[PDB]
Image (cartoon, rainbow, N blue to C red):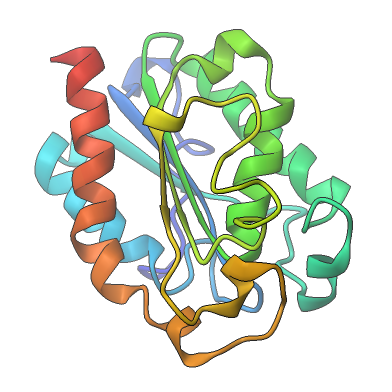
Length: 198
């Protein structure tokens, strides 16, 4: 695999359920299914919950993270939404009691948002927290994920990252989320898991 690819949910089963399952969608053109920011969040999550206590799953399969899909209505393709929807379904079926947390960068942040929007409310209720970096629909959705609570959403949108302000121009702030994925974003997700699970 490489640190850039994590299939802990796909490869896992009910007998080895983790308490927490993190599903993450990478940006356009990023490698593996975690890209650049996903591995730092994963390392922090495993310090907090232990290697056995958290499953990290990047969104792969039909999510090709094609730069042209950014221009589609929901900011990604229908196929990609179904891929992410199916991973939340699979988490829910394999491990009905795990707490779910989610994340995404750039097109993966629009994908997370469209997926959570379309999710059955009972599964959606289980997602304790979602972190979105360089969220391409930040302006259009006014910093929110449709049908999901504000208190469970943390958007990291740098000043000068123009994708947070309605365009698809890539500027240097868009490439500057490394600090956030190492610190505030995993801390937020851990705090949201601990508030549900203890």
